[PDB]
Amino acid sequence: GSDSRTVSELVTNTNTIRVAMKDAYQRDGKYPDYQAPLSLTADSIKTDSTGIAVAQLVQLGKLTPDEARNGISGDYIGIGGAITSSGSTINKGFAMELNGLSQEQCRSILGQVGDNWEYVAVGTSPSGSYDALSAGAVNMLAATDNTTILRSLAANGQVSLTAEKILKTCTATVNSITLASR
Image (cartoon, rainbow, N blue to C red):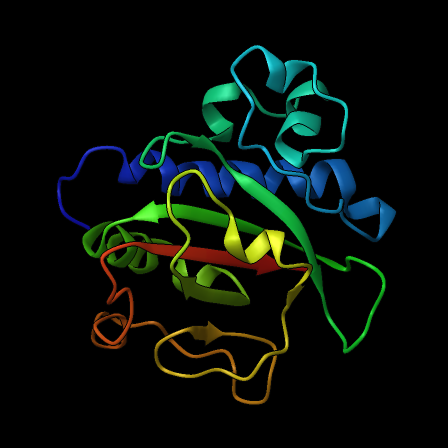
């Protein structure tokens, strides 16, 4: 991406969070349910005990508040469950949602991270909201298309998100990216 403020930090945070999520939870074989981080502060990320994943990671000492934050939206990063089969009742994956992105920010982020996640989708969740995560566990096996469900565990779902392909997405004025992994 271009020399645009904050995008490199958010991208790096996605990596840092991935490492921390694996360290905290992978041994359990399942990941935490979504709880909204949208009212957290730099204080309360250290104290909230309702099950917000970034708060858990900070309280485990595996992450700090700046590493948990989306500086583009000004929200702490949303993290919820993801499923790996139809009608599963276990979060066998996790999903993180990056909200409040301009077209350029969204494209830049996809150009840096896209092919490092086995599920990638683009939505329209604004700053202050996590529309995908609040809707439920993310379906990692939804069929891909060229605009919304970009990479998934569906048949032929590990699409290479080249610069050219990224031109077909992030096309709204307000965009969001959901990344998910086993």
